[PDB]
Image 1 (cartoon, rainbow over the protein chains, first blue to last red):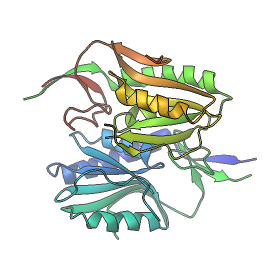
Image 2: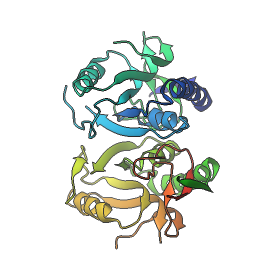
Image 3: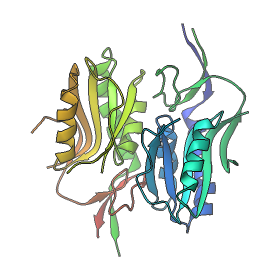
Image 4: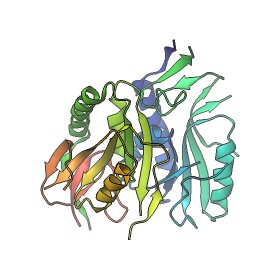
Length: 155
Length: 157
């Protein structure tokens, strides 16, 4: 039987997302940025974050090493931000980063809600090596849609 | 010189999403449903809705640009209870292709939930019926603009 323990409540996440959106907004205010959502896990964070940026942004989606869904827009001379729910090994991410740089963007930075212990400029929480679920993170397809994040002790 | 006027606040949307999720949760409690997000406009509604379903659901994504599928369903839908999630339905042309495409995969059932429905296949879950007006925000854009507003507004272009 799986055991879920509290970790980050909806409110903790909401406050952290607000904070990251403020840093981002203030750095990209005049840069007409493009936010890239890494499916499927980044989607909850992505919608919460982009909503808190108080000016129009362009959104795009990618999913994975090969790409199942690639970038469908011209990134040349655009300021790009990759949005991730979590970063651990960074293998998929390095592929995206390298792939996006070939399209000659004006710049590229990454925001991740969680970073397990290329530079990552915006970081929500640095976390130890633990099994987290919820808010986009799943365990064999389960718990992906929990509104909050929990520590999982697999059954 | 675009002019935006209030229409649906974050709170109105949150309340409507919660009521739709409650009906959906009861109807799909034991059906191990698959929720299909229609990108790009359905994404805000999709995350808000699926979050309020208090049991694990499977999520998947499709996107259309003649019809160009930039992203198709990446899972077996045979004998699965499927729900297509849309921010808005107007003409339903892309939607009709999706519906017909999904039915060839033999799902146990297929229903649609749309936050907005502008006044052929039935739409079982509907947030608000709206008159013919130009709305932006919460996934709806005007030439790529305003897509990420947290609320929905009426636009005078």
